Image: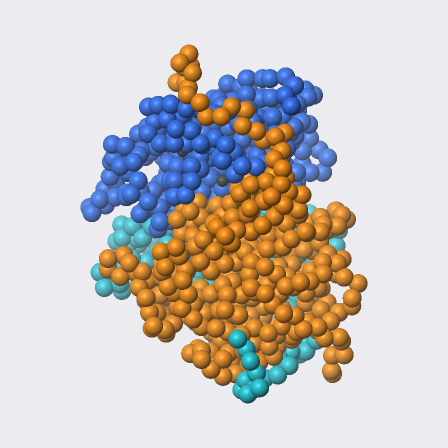
Chain colours: A orange, B cyan, C blue
């Protein structure tokens, strides 16, 4: 029975940015059309230049954020070009049936498939490849995961009948990676994903990542690729982790409104210091910036954040508020008449 | 001062099934009588036939689910037959005082003990052995843990004054296991729990399980022992983990109503993709099946799920709903006029 | 523009105790003055006498609990005596701007600094050192972390308009430690923090602690330093973990009211068995003791609790309530007419 709704083609953009969308809408349900192209390729994952045999949707880790509204249909064309070596598929945690779509989307290199799923559940959700068996974790931790956001048609709210609107949105995909080392402790390089598999599975089995990165590599979202904001802006930070827990924290800020389980039918928690993304999920936090300067956005296992790659920066423009915080006395020599024992 | 209430003897059944019970009841408080018999025995824990020196309540991992109502008394006869080698006891996280009952239930082989605890707290709760000191984790990770459910007398509700009723209930006990390996990486076998202890403690200390299983072994709840359901049924899935965190996910479904901390005085969260069972607790999720087919129920560390044992299946009978999901175009060769870069 | 409020100097006390404070107050906002003195020193961390090159605020792990009210200003003098070897600073997760204060408080040995932050966010919050880069995790896991509590001016409430008042408060700071071992597996000793660093970083990178302790050492809060309470007392247990997740559980009790994300703008959950402190946060639980005796307070990874150091005790005075729990029959030989198969 043909589905007779308007169609809208969406052009995806690379994370941490997000394709243009409306928050609140008075449009009715549409068939929202997306295309994802699998790309297997070697990628650089850390500041020392370590390479990795990655597998991606659309060439990025994470895959791009898709945004629709409650009641829309999502029609995804998944493409597996013949330059790839592996079969792939896609599982939407937002979707109902057939293992999230994985049981309807298995494609060999040289094939494509078209899946439609109804967006009946609001929130942010993981999507990931899941070919079967041990290939499921391997494809996911090789980079084959992203997220989809299903907004209420009226946009976000605080769970107490007040509208919430973001000025800016960023998507932070966190990736646990498992890179083999040689006898001397150096990371090993491989010429194909298949050649990396056996050694990689051994590292995976011990459940300790070698790297934990945002946007696919250590330092991806620092330096010149820091995330911009301004004092007074309400920023939505979507965070996903398809395989392993995370504990996001905005250093020098808070989560004003946090859906740590990621589902907008639940009221957000207020005023959090650190929240928790359970592996296999996406969550989201709103924050209104109150101070200018550099903020570091981390997982608050600080070892992961500082030493395995999992730090992003915000650079926030505006005027400093000395009522909220001030340096009363700059560093000075301890007074000779001090005690301090 | 004798307690003058009606007595009801309950016959426990092996997980993942649950003894017969009422959800809502107009019966008053009763003394609900249960018996648990400790059994130390070698068990098979994975598809390659690895054996393990297990210690169990009632011969199963997990121990059986006990179900009572708020205000009932629970009178447990704990039996430690003289064929066992170790002292054992029982700690109910549902109970108040004496380390959950552990300080009143320590029995040598050849002894039994009778503990009564009042079910003053609603929810699902862990029970476990806890003899003292380093024996506490060892007995728990050797299999000596289960769960108890204390239902409100009016049954479950959504926290907004609407009754919730399940058509079916399953109990998923997740077990982290720590099996020693020899110099070549093969799992070691032992002739007794005591002989396994020193080598097992060394693996335990590094906090990385070798196996993470549902119902005591990899593949326990797949193949012919898949969990049955039908389209339209509301299924309650109780999940426990006595020692280590888990992140349950129903692949192709959701948690319609989830008590991830497991306590029915709190309203459930709605529409979750993945939830979180903190180690040392039980949680519960309701889901109404909307699509037929195979569903995989996992912890969403996919390495744990696919490679360490932690996958169950549901086989759901009914009619496919093409409005919720459909394969618009089956796999086909990428059109020659396609781009895809 | 000078801030013209009354000033109040607070004398901090060593954990697990808490400086005197009011729960509800009709005082207006004050500038609450605190001093923290960094101390680098070797400390004993386990029952076998293992030593560790620690770095602390005020000589303790955790640093002391600071207590203020919503709307107060907190003026902290941070002192780094010239006997220390390292630069230090302080990041308050309760504060807004400048990386929580870290970007305004970096002091060399022989210096001090004065930071003021407005207590605009209610809850319990971590504070920690964060000098920069890989020094951030190293200083934190060397002991440089504590917590601050920002109470509502009306004190705590249940989120349903009922006041909650504690009779007693304890602060449990949990510390993950990473102690190097030699080729034979023995813990290594060092003459300075700098000399320990390279070997310690290698252990940190594998993300598995060697020790997980409360109040700075295994057994700190057992034996003669057990935590006292009485039947009928409502006890607030503040728990922090600056780097790694924890799952607190009171063995033989419950969490009557739990803010596991730690922020008093959110209603607490009721009747929990086990709760979850996400690494980089503090949470809090109220419990009214109903039974006398020993209680063990653990992280419910029981391996961590029994074998890596993470057990505290409460010793509770009062009268046993046989209605809540009783030993119906003491241990006895299994009756000859028993079956039990
Ligand atoms: Cu794939
Ligand atoms: Cu998934
Ligand atoms: Cu036992
Ligand atoms: Cu327990
Ligand atoms: Cu420091
Ligand atoms: Cu921090």
Point 39% across, 49% down: residue:
A307
**Is residue C10 in sight in this rendering?**
yes
Left or right: B19 as drawn, with respect to A51:
right
Q: Nearer the viewer, residue A261 or B196?
A: A261
Q: Quadrant of residue C98?
A: top right
Whole-percent x and y of residue A264? 67, 55
Quadrant (top left, top right, bottom left, bottom right) of the N terminus of chain C: top right
Left or right: A148 as drawn, with respect to C303:
right
Whole-percent x and y of residue A242? 51, 61
Q: Is residue A111 above or below residue C187?
A: below
Q: Is residue B144 above or below residue A40?
A: above
Left or right: B327 as drawn, with respect to A158:
left
Whole-percent x and y of residue B154? 71, 51
Whole-percent x and y of residue C230? 53, 26
Judged from this view, the residue extending furthest toward the right is A26
Point 52% across, 48% down: residue:
A313
Q: Nearer the viewer, residue C290 or B115?
A: C290
């Amino acid at each position: 029975d043909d589905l007779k709704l308007p169609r809208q083609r969406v052009d995806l953009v690379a994370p941490p940015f997000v394709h243009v969308h409306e928050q609140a809408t008075k449009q009715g349900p549409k068939i929202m059309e997306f295309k994802l192209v699998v790309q297997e390729k070697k990628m650089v994952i850390d500041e020392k230049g370590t390479t990795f045999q990655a597998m991606t949707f659309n060439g990025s880790m994470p895959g791009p954020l898709m945004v629709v509204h409650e009641g829309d249909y999502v029609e995804v064309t998944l493409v597996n070009p013949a330059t790839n070596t592996m079969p792939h598929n896609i599982d939407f945690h937002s979707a109902t049936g057939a293992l999230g779509g994985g049981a309807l989307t298995l494609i060999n290199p040289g094939e494509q498939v078209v899946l439609r799923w109804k967006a009946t559940r609001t929130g942010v959700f993981v999507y990931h490849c899941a070919p079967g068996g041990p290939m499921i974790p391997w494809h996911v931790v090789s980079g084959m995961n992203g997220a989809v956001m299903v907004l209420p048609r009226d946009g976000l709210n605080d769970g107490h009948g007040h509208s919430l609107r973001y000025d800016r949105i960023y998507y932070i995909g966190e990736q646990d990676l498992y890179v083999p080392r040689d006898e001397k402790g150096n990371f090993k390089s491989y010429d194909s994903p298949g050649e990396a598999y056996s050694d990689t599975e051994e590292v995976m089995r011990k459940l300790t990542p070698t790297h934990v990165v945002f946007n696919g590599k250590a330092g991806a979202l620092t330096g010149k690729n820091a995330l911009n904001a301004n004092v007074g802006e309400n920023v939505l930070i979507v965070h996903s982790q398809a395989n392993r827990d995370s504990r996001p924290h905005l250093i020098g800020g808070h989560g004003d409104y946090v859906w740590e389980t990621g589902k907008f039918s639940n009221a957000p928690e207020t005023g959090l210091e650190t929240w928790f993304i359970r592996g296999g999920s996406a969550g989201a936090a709103l924050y209104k910036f109150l101070q200018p300067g550099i903020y570091a956005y981390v997982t608050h296992n600080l070892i992961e954040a500082a030493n395995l790659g999992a730090t992003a920066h915000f650079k926030v423009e505006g005027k400093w508020n000395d009522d909220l915080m001030t340096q009363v006395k700059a560093p000075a020599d301890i007074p000779t008449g001090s005690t301090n024992e």
